[PDB]
Image: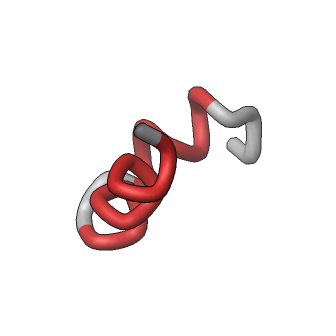
Amino acid sequence: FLPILASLAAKFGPKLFCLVTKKC
């Protein structure tokens, strides 16, 4: 689940990824 999620997060999702994984 995680490598495809990480790949799409890098591709066009980093705004949601940074808040969810607490890097904002």
Q: Is residue 5 above or below residue 16?
A: below
In the rendered view of the protein, which quadrant contains the C terminus? top right
Q: How many marks?
A: 0
Where residue 17 appears, as percent x and y from the top left, is 50, 43
Outermost residue, front direction?
A: 1
In the image, residue 12 above or below residue 21:
below
Vertical position of residue 24 compared to residue 13: above or below: above
Q: Residue at x 37, y 66 (%)?
A: 7
- Asked whether, in this view, residue 21 is left or right of residue 8, the answer is right
9 sits left or right of 22 in the view:
left
Residue 22: horizontal and vertical position, in percent?
74, 34
- Tell me which corner region of the image, top left, top right, bottom left or bottom right, holds residue 8: bottom left
Decide if residue 18 is on the left or right side of residue 10.
Answer: right
Q: Residue at x 41, y 38 (%)?
A: 1
**What percent of the width, then of the height, locates residue 11?**
28, 71
Along the viewing direction, whichever of 18 and 4 lies nearer the viewer = 4
What residue appears at the point 58 percent right and 28 percent down from the top-left corner?
20
Q: Given the current orientation, which residue lies at the most extreme top position?
A: 20
Give the residue furthest to the bottom: 11
The x, y position of residue 9, in whole percent, is 38, 56
- What sort of colour scheme is used for the picture? secondary structure
